[PDB]
Amino acid sequence: PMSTGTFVVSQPLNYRGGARVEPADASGTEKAFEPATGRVIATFTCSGEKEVNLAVQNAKAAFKIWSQKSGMERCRILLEAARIIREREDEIATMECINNGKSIFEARLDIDISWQCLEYYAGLAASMAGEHIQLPGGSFGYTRREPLGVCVGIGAWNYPFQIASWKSAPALACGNAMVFKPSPFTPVSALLLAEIYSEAGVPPGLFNVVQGGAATGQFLCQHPDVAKVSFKSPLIIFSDCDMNNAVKGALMANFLTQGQVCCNGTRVFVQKEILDKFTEEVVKQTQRIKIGDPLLEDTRMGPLINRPHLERVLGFVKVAKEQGAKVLCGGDIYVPEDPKLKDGYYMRPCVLTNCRDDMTCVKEEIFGPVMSILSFDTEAEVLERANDTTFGLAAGVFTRDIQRAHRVVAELQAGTCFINNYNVSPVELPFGGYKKSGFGRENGRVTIEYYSQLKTVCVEMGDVESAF
Amino acid sequence: PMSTGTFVVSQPLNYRGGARVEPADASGTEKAFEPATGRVIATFTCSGEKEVNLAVQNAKAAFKIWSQKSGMERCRILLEAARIIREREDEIATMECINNGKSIFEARLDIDISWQCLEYYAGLAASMAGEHIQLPGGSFGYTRREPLGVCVGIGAWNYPFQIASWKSAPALACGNAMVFKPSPFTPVSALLLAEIYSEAGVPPGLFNVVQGGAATGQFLCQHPDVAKVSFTGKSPLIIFSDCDMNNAVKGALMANFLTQGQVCCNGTRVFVQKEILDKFTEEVVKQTQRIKIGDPLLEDTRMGPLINRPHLERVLGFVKVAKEQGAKVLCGGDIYVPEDPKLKDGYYMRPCVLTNCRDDMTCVKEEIFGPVMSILSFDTEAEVLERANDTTFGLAAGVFTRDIQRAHRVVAELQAGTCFINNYNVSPVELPFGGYKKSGFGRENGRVTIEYYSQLKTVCVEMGDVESAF
Amino acid sequence: PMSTGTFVVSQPLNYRGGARVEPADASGTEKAFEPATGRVIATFTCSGEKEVNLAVQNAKAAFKIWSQKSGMERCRILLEAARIIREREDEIATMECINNGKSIFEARLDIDISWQCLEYYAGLAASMAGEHIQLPGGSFGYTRREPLGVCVGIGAWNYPFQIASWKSAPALACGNAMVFKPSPFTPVSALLLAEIYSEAGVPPGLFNVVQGGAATGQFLCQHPDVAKVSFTGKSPLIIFSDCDMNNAVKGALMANFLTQGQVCCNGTRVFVQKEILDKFTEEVVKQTQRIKIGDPLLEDTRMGPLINRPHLERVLGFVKVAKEQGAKVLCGGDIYVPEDPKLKDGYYMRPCVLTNCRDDMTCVKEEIFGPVMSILSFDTEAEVLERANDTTFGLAAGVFTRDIQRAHRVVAELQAGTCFINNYNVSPVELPFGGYKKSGFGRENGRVTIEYYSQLKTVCVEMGDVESAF
Amino acid sequence: PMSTGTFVVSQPLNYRGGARVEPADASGTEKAFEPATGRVIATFTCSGEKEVNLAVQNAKAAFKIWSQKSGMERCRILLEAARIIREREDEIATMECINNGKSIFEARLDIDISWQCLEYYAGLAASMAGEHIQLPGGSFGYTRREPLGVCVGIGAWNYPFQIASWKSAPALACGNAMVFKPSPFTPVSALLLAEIYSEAGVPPGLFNVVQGGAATGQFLCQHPDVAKVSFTKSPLIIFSDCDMNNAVKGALMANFLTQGQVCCNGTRVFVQKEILDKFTEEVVKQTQRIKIGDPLLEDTRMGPLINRPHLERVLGFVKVAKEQGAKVLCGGDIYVPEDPKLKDGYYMRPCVLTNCRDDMTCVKEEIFGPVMSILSFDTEAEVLERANDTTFGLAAGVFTRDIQRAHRVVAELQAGTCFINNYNVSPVELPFGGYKKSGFGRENGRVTIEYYSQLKTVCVEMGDVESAF
């Protein structure tokens, strides 16, 4: 039923005690947009400290109930929340494109992860166990992972529904309550999750939503009842690679999610030999990318999050030119054929060549559809030039020589490495966010630890053996 | 061998490239003592930034070698270091008492926990494995825990050799290098570990030692080549009227006077139910007055001296104010003069038992870090749980009651991370299962600490063609 | 909509390729009953060699498809099958009672386990991973748990739907196909599971059902394409003088008369201490005489009929001999005729309590599989432990004492696999944590059972040159 | 100090209560040999039932003690036993060759695994923990892995000390006692382990050794106090695009390590039509260079076969292979070493056969000798059909530079252990194809610990019983 250029927020954007609320006090006022049209979908209040307090006080209450429920009881509520998400998928995914701008194509994948995540932690809640050790003389010791209490989740604008799901699913599975503060850019989708949790059977206050910016964030972090607050990538193309897969990989790595992720492999090192053929093919393919209405099934490139952000990306390209880069295609305002999209935050995906490491476009993360093609001669050279990469990053190597691939992956300091592919998936996702992957056992174990604490009990069955 | 009142440091107290070194740069000077005699066992230089740099740079080099060795190779070196520790146990344990002041009795247990810890991580290094996930079309994904690089370990004075062992073992078993900064109170014992690691086959620079205080610590933390820095209401004891009095008294004494009560672990807030209050107090004072104070090297000694004179003066200060606030000193809390004249200038005091304690009292509010027991009276279960729930998760609590339901009910309500039913153990925070003897570490303790000293690398191998969205 | 004395089987009772089928060949013919009425609900064909072959061949086909689907795809199908089970719960629960005889009360708990179990393995299928080990010089090794192929599941009559689900869900989560062979006593309920799996989205043949007895079982075991066949002193209850009498009596009744006492899990050897013997016996008889015997479909019914006429004749046989051997029948152990004339020919009897029992007695020696309690007197802890430790590990035991030390000491000495302190649960063997309600399964139960239905494939990738010994 | 052609057993060959003992009764008598010389190193008594009973009764006692010790204590004893093994390594390896015939080279690697195994299980004993589940109303449930009791371990002659270590190390880490029956071929080495365990601090009767054959094995299995009894063709696909030298190295390793007397050995060598001639030429060249002789010599890579009947059987297989139409390219004949002490040793030259057919018994049956069967093939589809008749308990090795092909072949192959561009002749028990600096990971021990233990479950009720009635 929902379409581009029509949506307007009618209900309030805060959520406490299982219902939408207007904030009790303000830290300011913000406007949320429809990036495809430039339309204001909401003018909303940012939570003040009294408001922040009410939300924390409310979830503190819900925490006390939820923490007393068994893992099995919590598992059913969470599996239900996933069923509702799965059912209302197209509705949710639409709301997501409307406020964020990503393709319905991508937005659905985001929602798939979202319910998959909930099913994962629901499972873990039901199969939770501690350690038990037998001590000499019938005495024994045991452990239990207890929830922390009221956790704060800070959202991002690039994966709004998915970040909300990803933070709250392990949090609530542990028996905690969450107060979630989404990006002021994207305040809508989180309320859909909040509503779904209530519908699933979560006690009122367990997943609360406070809207706001920096001040709000600070008020949440400064709250005494808050237990815990939960808050360039290279692509090496060797001459011996499968050119078409390398080109496909480069495009995926740079233009998925409009290149508005830090995950994106924007530094494209291409070996001297294949440099000319690669560049020619990459420009050809980029010029075919479908820019338009994110709700259209054929659209692969939507608008950028907002006007300031778009201006910044266009600014990057102006400097890129100034510094000596050769704009091969795009990097300019795109005026879509449909007049409703006239004032949307659109631009054409950019491919830059003749890039050097000293260049700010090579140095800084742009957060837009901009590919920087850097030439290289030898394996030893790339590895020196590319190794300045943080562990929180990803790297991708394209070569038919398996030994070279493993050798390069071994030397690269990036946490996630892809041989003969590239996936633009969020950091949290295990196994580079490959589709039929699963989460394995370690991802959950580690994140469960983040949202819980280990209680240790020692039972003495005999007499105390005094040293004195 | 070594005896009390005779030891003096002869070699330098820093350690780089497998040998003892004098610091290149100076950031002041410190004196280390023999707490049993008051003697200066060392006047040493506090490492300067040029020195800190050398130690980090040396470890960075050693890291590059070690990180390339298999878990199996790393395991043999670590199992060897544990064998040497176990063999030189009394030598180590004695060197520990000489500088720290704890009884040889307790010092040995500390050393047992040190070699046990090394054998544990050695085992984990050899049995390390990642995840391997199969993907559609023959493509696959896998994971690897890699070391972080050069890790900094900051020591404490209460468990000097044990803190050094506890930080270094998980670090070195991940393939990391370590630069260790002991407490300038207890500089000596760490060098013994450093020597042992070299002897075991650790590459030169893998476990380096830099002496110093705050400045030295700051230089280590500020160093760009340092990957990670590992650092270091009051603990209650609830005694119900239905408990086994003798075990409760034994437990209270253990909880307050082990390690001279110089740990934050110690259960110093002793809540006693109104009925048993009089009998408990009478028995606890009787038993406390029997505690053997003296030479920590003596096998019969259960109470040694306090770490230093400023620290002793502070504990004596707390007692002075406690009686000013209205507490009743039942025994001790005064300067003790041992029979032994070599022991004359040692930092000794008689273990203290205080009664008529109120929650408003600073002795009940603040952690003293001395042998001082605060006895607080209570009437009901509901009352204690209110009064004693202002306890942090990083603390420990002990409950004494013959009613099993009550015990579990109390343990459930208490916010402490480690709870003991019908006992109390004063073991460091790091130790799983309340540091009970012959316990083991289970699997989770190691898993969690390995995570602290490592990072997860993920690799995705594509067996087919790239599926383009465009 | 379904009721007692009305139901008759209309469709065939074998399942192949997503539909009910009549067996291709016969190994014989059986009659399935309504135990509450004595009615024949179905006269069915036992599967012959050719039919067993067809089900295996059909499952082999389904296996090839399913095994190629990801754990995530298999997880959705299983989570769906659990949703359908949960939704049609009362329909299945009812159908279960009609053929088996257990109370609708107990039948629901069985069905709750069924869908809980499917949700568990669905979770495990989605989170499956192997090990990845790094080797010198960039070479690597990894592992994967692969399904075995076509597995066979053999049913029991005491938990027909539950044991059907318990065997199918793990085998299928591994990516296997299964051929289930229900007890010829209880053929019906399994077909409901088979139908649900189809409805969920399992490929036709993934979970086939072949009816039959021993010959069908033999044909399944002898089949060359069958990868694995999954099959299905007496349990004591020590009641000490210092315990909580009412909980001990409640526990004794639960332990003996749940599932009409037709489980091997049931704690039928009740050791009672000489002192409390008289009070316990008096209370247990009083409570037993209050047990509601009748229509299993009635919500108030706690005791239904026994599985069949031969089965009942056997239990009453054991009672006849028990009094011949010197036992004192305190209540029941006789043919019961319910007030509802429809239940006139059902397989009913009054729950029995026997006293003055000796270890030499066959009622104490043999498992009866009926509502019969054997009360044995004892004087001391040392005595019981001697008399009761002729217990196999595949059994359960229960101890009632207020002395925690005594409880743990007894549990430690007892050779039973599952021990209950101050309670008793009659849950199937498979169930972790004594089948307590809000328990969960933990991680180990699943790990171990996944290993049963899978095999470890190991792959070694050489990145360098082969190092020849020659 | 020990050498070939000198050793003779002087002490008895059973071990009970921390001592070597002569069997109380007999199930027969066997002769043990020095395969390098043909010498009888021992004429010993096979254990009767009274003797088996004594070993079990003694082990039952030691169990009751060992099972009551902490996993922490057990771990120290086991880490000590590994230190002693590691220290007396050369003595043990020497003794192993003397009775078995394998090279000092391989015999050491066997002993390395042996002490590595013990260190692994020692670690697991110390870090053992059960599950603890919280239940509504303060009630709780927990689990513990308990030992089974007296376990029986049946040895093999190909890895005598290693099989003993591999069975005893997990069982003893659990808290069980073990009665071990070595192969009547290889009695000696197991007693060295039994002695080391005692020296380490194991209670007397915790690891007992009863010498014997089938009757003795049967007596052990039939014993009511015995809790559990633990008991003991592989293809190699060479594609034309492979690295020839690594493929040849791999083929030799796969066929002639341990004198080819393992079921692990990749004896069916499928070679592509194109590289067939170059491969065959190189493999024969390399095989003819293998150093046959005194297993105690550091340069020796091929020792003698386990015994005369076994050698005759392998020579028999070669006779029939050429009768069936195979082309003997080298060896497969009685070898007479230059050293006269070795004159009556059970030696033969490693054999390479070509013109093999799938119908041939040498391709069908496991030979247990140094015999390589070279089979030609044209396409990937063909090999995969011909080689798929492989059991999961087997290994397979693929050699190809095409990574896609390698994974594709490994995926289709039914073998449990697959190697890409290598082949390792390691026992079945070993995780990650028995690669040297591999480790054991965590699953191998978990699964084996389960074999030698049982899960005890305890449920503590903190409240009142909720009666259905």
Image (cartoon, coloured by chain):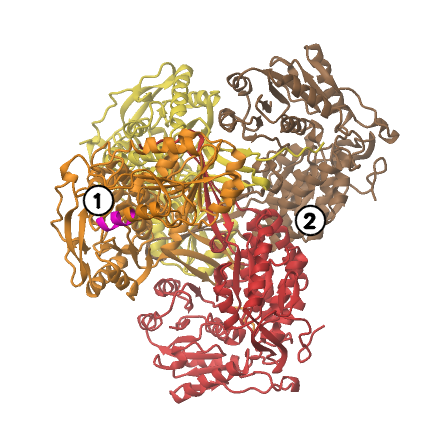
Chain colours: A orange, B red, C yellow, D brown
Indicate whether residue A310 is drawn in magenta.
yes
Q: Main secondary structure of the magenta part?
A: helix
- Chain where mark 2 sits: D
- Along the line of sight, which residue is nearer the eye, B443 or D77? B443
Instruction: Out of C265 and A359, give the one closest to the viewer.
Output: A359
Q: Residues within 10 Å of mark 2 (few under 14, many from 20)?
A: many
Name the secondary structure under disc 2. helix
Q: Is residue D328 above or below residue D219?
A: above
C68 over A334 or under it: above or below: above
Choose between C161 and D2: the one closer to the eye.
D2
Q: Which residue is mark 1?
A: A345
Q: Residue furthest bottom?
A: B324
A215 relative to D17 in the view: left or right? left
Relative to residue B195, is residue A443 depicted above or below? above
**Identity, as a three-letter code, of the amino acid under mark 1:** Tyr
Subunit of label 1? A
Residue A117 lies in magenta, yes or no? no
Secondary structure beneath disc 1? loop
**Dot 1: few (<14), some (14–19), or many (≥20) neighbours within 10 Å?**
many
Q: Is D51 rendered above or below residue D66?
A: above
**Residue contact at pointers 1 and 2, CB within 8 angstroms:** no
Task: Write down the residue under mark 2.
Answer: D197
Residue A262: image location, x then y, percent: 35, 47
The alpha-carbon separation of the residues under discs 1 and 2 comes to: 77 Å
Point out the stretch of residues depicted in magenta.
Answer: A307-313
- Front label number (1 vs 2): 1
